[PDB]
Image (cartoon, helix red, strand yellow):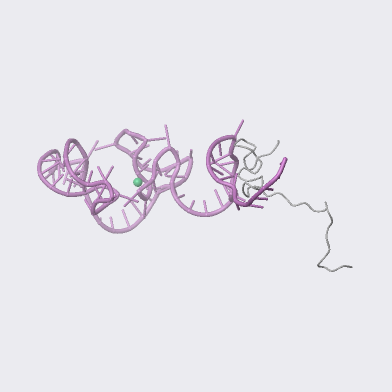
Length: 48
RNA sequence: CCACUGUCGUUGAAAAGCCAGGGGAUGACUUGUGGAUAGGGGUGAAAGGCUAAUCAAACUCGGUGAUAGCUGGUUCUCCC
Ligand SMILES: [Mg+2]
């Protein structure tokens, strides 16, 4: 009933997603939270 | 036709040659043209040799984005 220009989802409704490997300042650069080179840091790795 | 020795050359004149020497040179000889044998198959006076500069299993395409506990890389910012 407002404008299309001024509706908001409200606080807590939306969270921005994490993007791994986008620099130092993001807290997820380089390894992207995977730590260092073991089986878990590799691509198709799982928790069997 | 071959390839024993050496020098040279080794981003070569050349992805195997040159030069100087060397061996066979009527023979199990060399060579032209066409054909046959096809990949775990061929062919081999046998070196795992050769099968188009590719051979302890050719090449191309496809399964296929094979798999890779391995290596590398992984991109804006500030606060706790
Ligand atoms: Mg060859």
